[PDB]
Amino acid sequence: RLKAIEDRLEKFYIPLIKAFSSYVYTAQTEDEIETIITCRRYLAGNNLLRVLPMHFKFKADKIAGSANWTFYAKEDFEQWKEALDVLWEEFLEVLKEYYTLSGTEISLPEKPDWLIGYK
Ligand SMILES: [Ca+2]
Image 1 (tube, rainbow, N blue to C red):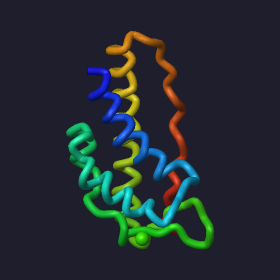
Image 2: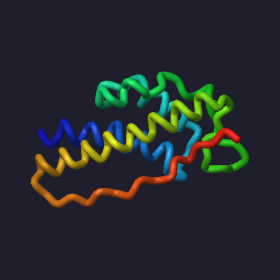
Image 3: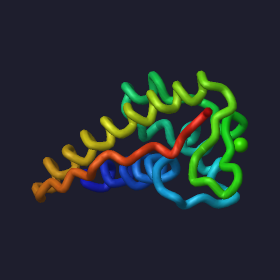
Image 4: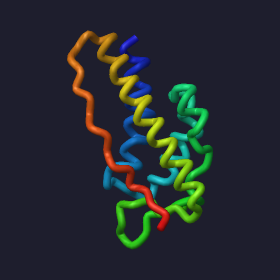
């Protein structure tokens, strides 16, 4: 099943990676992240589920036109930094698995800067 693995990439890994690394942001983004980390946990690997926070909306905001997520508590910033790094490692493995299965050539993307801060 190429489809099963494509759904993990398209419905979980890619949107969550983009939410924390691409400049795209809407009035729906915090709720979309909440949805990914609750409703779409069934698409995550067990390693990531160990560290992925359950809650996000009330822990951070984008302020002043910045692309950065501003965390209010250092501890939440640290939890998210750790989880994003795990998310990225899982993502690259799921990409490798997709290409192993599809038989096509690997173009592994470079890791982005996480758009997160607290200080
Ligand atoms: Ca918020």
